Amino acid sequence: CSSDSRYKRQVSGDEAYLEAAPLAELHAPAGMILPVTSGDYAIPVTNGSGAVGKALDIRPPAQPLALVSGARTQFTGDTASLLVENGRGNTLWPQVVSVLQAKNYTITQRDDAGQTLTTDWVQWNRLDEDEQYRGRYQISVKPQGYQQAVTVKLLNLEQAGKPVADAASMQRYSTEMMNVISAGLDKSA
Amino acid sequence: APQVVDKVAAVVNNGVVLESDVDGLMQSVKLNAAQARQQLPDDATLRHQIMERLIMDQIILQMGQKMGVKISDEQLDQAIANIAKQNNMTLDQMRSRLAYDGLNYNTYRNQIRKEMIISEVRNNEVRRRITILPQEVESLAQQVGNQNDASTELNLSHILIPLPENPTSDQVNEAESQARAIVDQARNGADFGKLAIAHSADQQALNGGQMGWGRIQELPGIFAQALSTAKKGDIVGPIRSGVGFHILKVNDLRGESKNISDAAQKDRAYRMLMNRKFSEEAASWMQEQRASAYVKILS
Amino acid sequence: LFNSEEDVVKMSPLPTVENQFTPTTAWSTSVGSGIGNFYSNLHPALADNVVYAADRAGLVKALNADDGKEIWSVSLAEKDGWFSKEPALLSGGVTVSGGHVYIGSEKAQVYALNTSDGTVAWQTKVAGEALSRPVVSDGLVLIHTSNGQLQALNEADGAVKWTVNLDMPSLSLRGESAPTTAFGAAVVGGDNGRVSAVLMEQGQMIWQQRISQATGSTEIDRLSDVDTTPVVVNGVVFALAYNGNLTALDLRSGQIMWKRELGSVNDFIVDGNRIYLVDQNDRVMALTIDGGVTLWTQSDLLHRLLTSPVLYNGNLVVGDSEGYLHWINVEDGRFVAQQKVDSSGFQTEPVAADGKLLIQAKDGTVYSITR
Amino acid sequence: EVPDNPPNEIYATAQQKLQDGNWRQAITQLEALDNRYPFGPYSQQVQLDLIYAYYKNADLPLAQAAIDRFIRLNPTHPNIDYVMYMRGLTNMALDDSALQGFFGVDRSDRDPQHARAAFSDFSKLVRGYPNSQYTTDATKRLVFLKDRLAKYEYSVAEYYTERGAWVAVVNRVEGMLRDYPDTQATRDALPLMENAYRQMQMNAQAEKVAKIIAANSS
Amino acid sequence: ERVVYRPDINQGNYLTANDVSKIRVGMTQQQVAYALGTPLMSDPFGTNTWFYVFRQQPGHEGVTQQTLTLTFNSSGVLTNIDNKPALS
Amino acid sequence: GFVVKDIHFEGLQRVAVGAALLSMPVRTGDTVNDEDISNTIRALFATGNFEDVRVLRDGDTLLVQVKERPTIASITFSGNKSVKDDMLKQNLEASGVRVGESLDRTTIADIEKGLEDFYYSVGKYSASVKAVVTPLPRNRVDLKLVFQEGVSAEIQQINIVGNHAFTTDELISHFQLRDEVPWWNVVGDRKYQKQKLAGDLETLRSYYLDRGYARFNIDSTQVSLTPDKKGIYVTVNITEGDQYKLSGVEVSGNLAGHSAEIEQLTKIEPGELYNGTKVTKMEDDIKKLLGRYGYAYPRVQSMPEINDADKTVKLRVNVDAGNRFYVRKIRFEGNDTSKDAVLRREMRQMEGAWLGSDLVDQGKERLNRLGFFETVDTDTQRVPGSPDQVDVVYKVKERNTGSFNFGIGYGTESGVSFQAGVQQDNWLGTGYAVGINGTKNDYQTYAELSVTNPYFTVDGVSLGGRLFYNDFQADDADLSDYTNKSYGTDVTLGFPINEYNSLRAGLGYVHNSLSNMQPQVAMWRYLYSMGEHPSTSDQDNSFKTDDFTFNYGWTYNKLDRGYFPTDGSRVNLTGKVTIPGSDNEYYKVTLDTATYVPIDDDHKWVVLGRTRWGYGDGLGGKEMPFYENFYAGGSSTVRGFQSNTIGPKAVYFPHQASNYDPDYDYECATQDGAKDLCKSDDAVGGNAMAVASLEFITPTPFISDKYANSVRTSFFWDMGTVWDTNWDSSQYSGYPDYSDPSNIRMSAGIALQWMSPLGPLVFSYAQPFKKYDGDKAEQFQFNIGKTW
């Protein structure tokens, strides 16, 4: 019945495990040894730092859809690449440009010679977030073997007027821009 | 406007017939007709028979592929003797193939491979179907006596109106009417070769149904009793043998009183018995395969 | 539970015919309870103008052919009361030869009643249910039990002269093939689909040859039973298998001469240069003997479970599961006449001999048909 | 419930319903996509969203089945660490209860099967992918699960101390020392082992356990 | 004073005079395990010692215990046998 | 000979363009002829993914037009009635056809035949199958399989050849496969199943070996179909052999010192008939006896030495006990709610001790008798790499041990009203038995709490406590009407004395205070016995009593389960006696009994005999207080009667009520209209009570086994009587003799019990065919909670 906006992107638990007591070893007295450990329940010492408890976003990692005919689509750290097929050729760059013109995004740089462009800012009206993200993106098309391929990269992401560089957010809103591009290309076709 | 280069003309058991095959045999039969003086019918009636021959060829080729039968290069070398008619015209190169396909090598070599593979698998299956009985051999040999009785040699043209192995009476009367109409046309003055190209399920339809010169005893019997009473050019009405209705025309005949002087007659009688058995079992098995096989003509 | 949930509508309707003559029932006589709903081979036997009939429990009865009047009756159901009154489960059909009346039984018994009054001359235990029709020849009585064993009882005293084993599949059709006399041999069928020939002296197998295509996936598609009687003519054996081929074989060599996708479990007829047949679907057909070419076919009775045909007065006669007798012209499938004889169905083969046609209904009533 | 629109529109609706926060209709749409279009531009994405929605909807058995199928079909998938983390989460989730948690009941005495499975999955994740984004939370959850398992063993040993089965007590505490040496439950159990040794008049072993206690309780 | 039903608490592994008489010094661990069975209790604190305890508490009748301590060497060869047939 | 500038694909839906290009003989290069295009088309089709392939040329561009084999959108099995969709769906999936997979139209016939084959495996040989392919918009297809199930094949005969000792009818009477179905056996059928013929052959073999036939042999078996394939014939060819007698049984091998008992197990009467099942039972008994001593994995094999000449059989039994196994760990699985100790304290097998298996079974039955778990199973697993140790694992499925009762009475007509109650037997998996009850009205208040620890001491000593409060005074005391206010406490301690018997002792205190009672014969008789001398012509009176009692009890419990028992008997005796010092003195005792006797090996059909007795009386010149009286009737004691209606009825003296309403709604003895003693229908109960009941429990006909444990149906016959032993029959000769116990009420009907989420629910319809004047009938009754 009753619900809260944050039931999404949250762990289905009480977060009590963060209060568990730390593990400490036992000292072996002189003249004897402690029984040899099995090593079945050993916890490796990982020095990584990351979100814990409610601060960890468990939303599935947004993978590029690759709607327009293609394969070996990928999502890098801050950039995303989609490989296309079916004889697009140089005509890929016009279509890409037209697609991003259909979104009336604020394109700031337009270098047709290098098949590159850059926008100022776009916003996302997501019902999933308590605060709406926004990011600055650069898109390009480059030749690969037989055909051209599109790439979309994020300059930075911002929340509430301050920057954010979380890997999950970067991946999510690059798959967002990549899906936008792929859907536009498919619609054009 | 876009131009169609090739397409699938027929779908068979996991195979396809391409339009580059129908056209090839179309040109082949047209060239043979022109050299033989025998006029041939309209595009569609000729097309249906060519498509049927290609369905039967694709079925047999897939059976050969399934059964692990392959052909050697020396087999192609030997077929060059007769398939290319090098013995008749002394030249090896493909410049003799002036009619069509620009004197290409691979196309005609693959065509020959297609014929050798079909013939090989046909022969193997039909031979494995033959049953020979000593009693029949003795009977036929004792028939081969009294100055080689029935030494008549015949060149005949044959037309087959097919019926399924288990036909319905409706189909029976339909085939009966068709066969009687063809027989009436042939007897009234219609050229049997033209009738054969238009109306025939036999493999030899594309060649006009000519069986070539043979000896009467070689007939499966279904034709010899009726055929003993017939002159050059006569038309023989419909008959049956399991595969459908049969119609025969006596193209030519030649008889002589030669006698081979049993020690050497038993082997010859076995040869002719094997010839008749192969002809009948071949027709029966090719009809069975046609009924069984999956096919969907495409248009 | 529910009696209104299971039914398949695959029965042809009663054809309309203009009868060229008026079929008549010369006489009729009740013989016990009859075959009943069980599938059996029991049928009358005609011998010297005497009609011998039997019953599933056993009521062996002898009736006059002329007016169905009886001359002697007996019951083989626990005559001495060894255990209550158990049924004899007779299912061998009446055989008549040499003054003896041979009958099989599903209790693995073979009775050899007498002609003069019915006294049981001898009773022999056999390898199993004597489903086959006894065949009398060369002083021997051949039986083919349900467990796949051909036995040759001695005619005089019933002693088993010899025995032969035949392979039995995991599933088959109820019934067994009756051997044929041939020339000092015995040509028999089998549930495995292999026709066999055995010499009359002992069980030395002469030849065996497969008759069924049996290209199925599961057991029900491999039903290759040869439950018909092989017919020997001029040294060629005609055999017919269920879901198999109507084939002709050399009597001694055993190699097939020709084959045709036609199956049945009802005995066929070989007359002159023609073969009259009834397929498993109740399709009356006529072929030729030299080669299979279906001279004509009839389908008006399709899926009306028919009995085996009999040649009578120059025309073919067949009974049906509803008690209607149908006459068919030999030259063509046109019906020559039709009659209603009994309310209970006709299952077992009719008898046509000495210019007289007899049949027995499922209820045991023996009918004589004339004109 | 599910119309026959192309896969694009079904996926768009599923994404919209996931963003809104309704799991049941979103579950229906993703299941429709998975069953009707098992290949295409959307494949695997549907399965990841199905796992997420099953977890958030408390459909834990279905989440386990989906995770198993995804793991056995796409072992090389770059985001398989997320799948293993969700496996650990759904196994830990099966180890909890609502009413008992509401009443403040210590559940470490109940069945440890699900805790053991969660520990196995989280250990697999941490060892296989040290640099994953979920490794820190996985390590914290491992430390908690280890403490829970040691507490279960301590509960069993305490019961057998009450019953008077001294061999069982000694074996249980020895298993604790060999399996969970560094947990607090092991430190609490050592006195039970010493008492069990003394009740069987095995003074030499009680002396050794007392030496351990003196050398470490300080 | 304690008039309530208490089940028998059997603890350890069954010992018989014949089995205890089958083992002798110099026996390897495999032979001892074959003669007496796997011990339900060993020394986990750094010694090759096997404890064969035989407890029986039929109820309120009083507990009895026989404890057989087998001390092996580093090579697994039995070195000392100490049999106590009753509690102190 | 032309350069391919570009390759464009059309029609690809499932096959990625990359895969198709890899499947191509062309590499966007050049040097291409017509034959290359033909080979490309042939290769594309050879991949088996395309139904139609076409290649077109547009200038220097290659346009590849492909029609992918349509995709299955949905599969709908329509018309199937006997084969269920899931089964048939699994079979079709196994055949390689599933939603999404490309539909190779060259195999539809095949799958159709496969389906028919499955029907053949179901016993439907004359069944027809057809596939209808309906084209959809996105080049998908719905594959609807229409089924015409044929008439099932039935067995026309089962024949046995070679049987002379036993008639065919008797032999086949035990078979599952049946030739004839008795007219009264509407649920039977003549269907044939291969697994059943296999079991019937095993049944025949066992029958012949169990009646003395060591040489019995089944020569062969034949199964045949009728030409039309709607009848089935079965034949069994057998060889009886001859009857044999036992000469002796001699045991050999490693008996592990248990020769005396094993030899006592293998006892035969000299010259008895051979018996296979007896030999099997001897083997099993030897295995069980060895298991009692820890030999968990012995090998016991018996071989009969036959003597055909003498026709006698001598059994040689070889026994090898093996190693004595020890338990290493005892593990419990499935106790997600129950605390681990709750399960572990029921164990008779100690963890680190030698195995006996008898103890393991004892622990299993203890857990079953506990009633907290729906299913309990045991598994003794050998420890890997250990020749002498095992792990015992108990797998349990937990139940809903709680039950809830709720309702609302008059509503808001007079103030507010409601009724509530909860009862838990495993509160929060702690093993505690907790219970709260309450009711609120303008005419009554009631509260009751109960908490019991079944294991207050490890040995099983239980400690329990109970508080209760009850009131009838109206709010604000509008008028001096009948009032009854009581409260009290009760502390009880129980302890076991056997594996099945336990005793209970405790102390209770109860305070009662009645006032403004209506004068009636029984209550005034009791009050006179107490020494009180209340008036009879007016309703103003008062009475107060404090009571201390010693409570005792004894419970014997050997039931199969704690819920829906199928075997065993349970007896529970309770009683109380006032401690000297109470305002009134008496004793009371009650005795409940419930016996279950199974009739089927599966325990599906059971006979339940239930009984209840009660007697109480005063000690000195006093009498048992009328508020301790026994009551009968209702869903708990005698179904078909209104609750607490059986027994003596109140007799009122003429008197004036404290109120006089104009509705005439007052007892018959009201002074306004009456001046003589008159009876009523108000049940008052009696100090002696006896009730009995016989029930026949049957399987529920319209539920699958998945709910068998959840529903119980029974047919019951109940008897019950209540009487007042002190009723002065010498006086009051004009009224029924309430001291006579012969007035036995009876009822008969049908009852249904369901383990609903709110606990047990009991419905019953009972006709009370025997009743006496004043008894209120209630044919249909509904109840919540543990009944009796």
Image (cartoon, coloured by chain):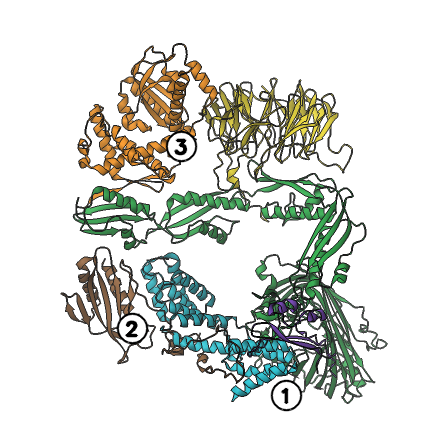
* Up/down of F494 relative to E36, above or below: below
Foreground disc of the pair 3, 1: 3
**Cα separation between marks 2 and 1:** 75 Å
Instruction: For chain D, give the colour.
Output: cyan
**Do the numbered discs 3 and 1 sit on residues whose CB atoms are within 8 Å?**
no
On residue F477, which mark appears?
A: 1
Label 3 crowding class (10 Å Cα cut-off): few <14, some 14-19, many 20+?
Answer: some
Instruction: For chain C, give the colour.
Output: yellow
Q: Chain of mark 3?
A: B
* Up/down of F253 relative to D137, above or below: above
The residue sitting at 48% across, 73% down in the picture is A39
Label 2 crowding class (10 Å Cα cut-off): few <14, some 14-19, many 20+?
Answer: many
Q: Which residue is mark 3?
A: B288
Q: Which residue is mark 2?
A: A170
Q: On the image, which quarter does residue F171 sit in? A: top right
Instruction: Identify by letter the chain in orange.
Output: B
* Up/down of B192 relative to D113, above or below: above
Say left or right for F694 vs C222: right
Q: Chain of mark 2?
A: A
Q: Chain of mark 1?
A: F
Instruction: For chain E, give the colour.
Output: purple
Identity, as a three-letter code, of the amino acid under mark 2:
Met
